[PDB]
Image 1 (cartoon, rainbow, N blue to C red):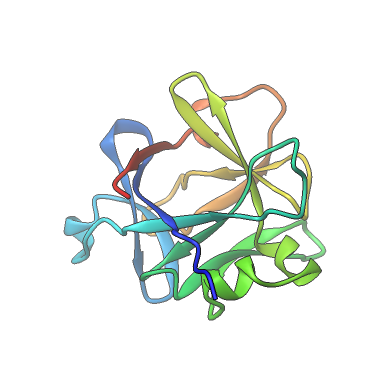
Image 2 (cartoon, rainbow, N blue to C red; image 1 turned 90 degrees about the horizontal axis):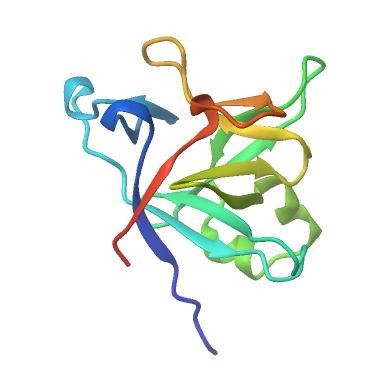
Length: 151
């Protein structure tokens, strides 16, 4: 049976900060200062969700763990889960929780939660704070990421 070919990136935030992982969290900063390397992050399209946008899954560690929304009474947050990116690619409605709409903002990219329209991936404001979701209308530096494709 055919296999998809995931795209890979190094993903940066403002001021050359990079996405990386430690202790089960997706973090942003200088990976080496936190005893890590910049994470090779992969994506695959969610083909069945909305063919008019660019829905994707976001995975770390060769796509072994993927970013998901989790609903709380204070709104959605994000966490990495033990679900691999091929399991999402071949899945169904349960994959919507792991889906983000990828769009351009000039030379940057923004990622909107498919499960929570209007909520976007947001960089941390505190050291060692995981990536956040924020409800942003007017695009800003807080939601702008830089995808540098490697595969």
